[PDB]
Amino acid sequence: VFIKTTSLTYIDGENGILRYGGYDIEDLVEHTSFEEVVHLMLYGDLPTKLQLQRLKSALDEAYEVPQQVIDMIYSLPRDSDAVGMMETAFSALSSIYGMPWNKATNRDNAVKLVARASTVVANVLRAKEGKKPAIPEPSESFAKSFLKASFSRTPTEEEVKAMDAALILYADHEVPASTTAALVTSSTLSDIYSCVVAALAALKGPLHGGAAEEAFKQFVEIGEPDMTESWFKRKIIEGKSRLMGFGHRVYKTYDPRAKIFKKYAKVISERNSDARKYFEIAQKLEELGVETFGAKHIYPNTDFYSGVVFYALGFPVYMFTSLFALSRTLGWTAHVIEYVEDQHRLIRPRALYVGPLKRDVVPIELR
Amino acid sequence: VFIKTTSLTYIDGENGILRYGGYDIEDLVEHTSFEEVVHLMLYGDLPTKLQLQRLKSALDEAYEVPQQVIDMIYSLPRDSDAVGMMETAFSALSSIYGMPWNKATNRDNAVKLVARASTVVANVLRAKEGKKPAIPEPSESFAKSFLKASFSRTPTEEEVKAMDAALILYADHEVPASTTAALVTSSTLSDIYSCVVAALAALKGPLHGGAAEEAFKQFVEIGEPDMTESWFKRKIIEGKSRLMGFGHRVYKTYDPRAKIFKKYAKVISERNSDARKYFEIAQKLEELGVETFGAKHIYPNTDFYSGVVFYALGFPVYMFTSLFALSRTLGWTAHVIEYVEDQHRLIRPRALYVGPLKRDVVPIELR
């Protein structure tokens, strides 16, 4: 059931093609940047030099949020689900910054929102690690500012590029329950931050979030590359567990996102023996997996190497769905702007009554 | 489009009938209690004496939440929308208390949730008023515990009864965007508190929340009963403004809830000259309104006198939708339990691509 039209994202699952706004994902990753893709999704084209300068200034000025928002993150239990911590922070952002829908300013509000997602996700990691807070600051890119804030160290250029690619790769895809919850909430003209709140509330559910985690947890369980064949023979072949990070409801080929996350995984994993080990296990499972499942059109999906990237960057496994959400704030905001501006109606379905027929209240003594 | 089946609520809009679980609303209000209606909605029948005792103990033990939840409420700007403050508090409750879906414990989790809604709404009012926090404590009823916590004074029996009625009256009705957002979020097996978060995010939008406020604001604008005819002749007849709190998409008669909110309004308004004045204005507008619109099947709706009740109890106008939400946590939770247990599937609709055809990334110099 088509819930809306979109100009945002095109997917050809037979051919393994994904495009944003007519541009193929690989072309966007190699030759653009998350900032540029932000402009594409909100404004419908890649930006000129001047338009990009202005968008970058708008991002920069938005990073800072009130200290109350950070305090909230840091007052939650440190073992709380990171997506829930985001949910809470975005609720507070909605209460502080939420504005009515307005064509002249919707995209500007979305841009500020994406900046603030960066601040939120960095501080969720830092709260859960017991580190001091850090607010992103201007740098040569959104991906670098995010990494600097997350880790308190200047990242290398190859780390910057891999984060930038990950931001683009997960920006938008299909209409999952998170995007649906955002749409419902936008149907009442609740503010864009509250549309994201709803999306996160849905994301927290284990039938939606947790895919990049469950994939990478295979690798962790294997532990060492020379144990992969055994774990595969035991867990997948003999015990017919699903191989996580394989298979897709739309793609009948390699997910075009998978190949890309892999390329960046290979580059940034080689520095650290730990990240390299998991990259090496994942590569071996990829082979055993395609040898076993490829003839069935079951290939790596976007979630198979994304953990390997995030892990190589220095992110714990508990951050993986939050890092997905950081990226997907772009598609969430762009979908709700399209929906409100072009296709609005209040979402109010019906429930069919199948319950009891008329009966009278009996006094409680008689029950 | 029927999104689900339900055994919860029956509505006959031609005949002005509303029933929960086969019991007519008026019969439930006169002869039961919110606690009993909680049991009805979660378990499918009015409770015996023992079942009611156990439910009351479960409510009592749940009121207390961690101090971090109260601190969050109190760290938001005091002029923040009360429904947003609830959204934030419930996000924090989700992070602290959220559990997976489980048939043996779903209803117990819902009961604890409704108790905690009481704590949240009392402290939202108290934060916005600049008063010290108060946690509900056991008393002879949920309605009284809520009022004691909100106002730091023992309420009269007639005040208790009016609050109890209001809790029942707004418990469940149709499948508005708030209930829809809850359902979407439950589709991923996000926890029940996060299902409520989503519902609140949708409620915050002005096409959903704010109805009891906008109705009562008429009365405030009129100011004095002897000005009602004038305001009516000017604003409704000459300026064809909608009369708020009149009209309904389903009822072609008096909303069965309207008559009931009116009865309790009359009783508790008479004590205070201010509340009495607004009751007297509302009664006069009711008359002018039915004289003008009744032949068109446009009659008072549930939102016309509910503000008069809440105001008479001592609640500011900015609390009215939050007091609706307090009540509606019951229908929200009961709908999502029905949906998950009996009718589950992941909610994943589609978007039709109507955007640009294939194009190549141009270098930014060429843009």
Image: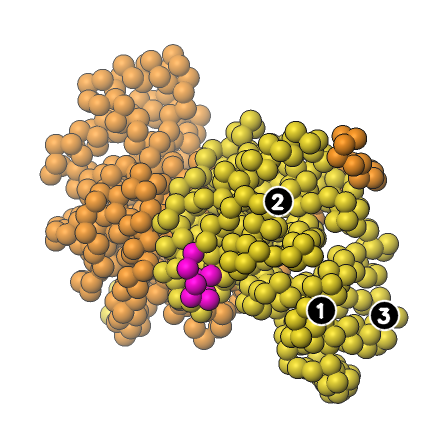
Chain colours: A yellow, B orange
- In the rendered structure, does residue A129 fall within the stretch colored magenta? yes
Q: Amino acid at mark 3?
A: Gly
Kind of residue at disc 1: Glu
- The residue tagged 2 is A140
Which residue occupies 56% across, 35% down? A57
Q: Quadrant of the C terminus of chain A?
A: bottom left
- The spot of residue B91 in percent (x, y) is 42, 56
Gap between marks 1 and 2, in whole Å? 24 Å
Q: Earlier in the sequence, mark 1 or mark 3?
A: 1
Q: Residue at x 80, y 36 (%)?
A: B362
Residue A294 circle label: 3
Q: Is residue B293 above or below residue A35?
A: above
Mark 1 or mark 3, which is nearer to you? 1
Q: Is residue B283 left or right of residue A153?
A: left
Q: SS at mark 1?
A: loop
Checking the image for residue A270, the label placed there is 1
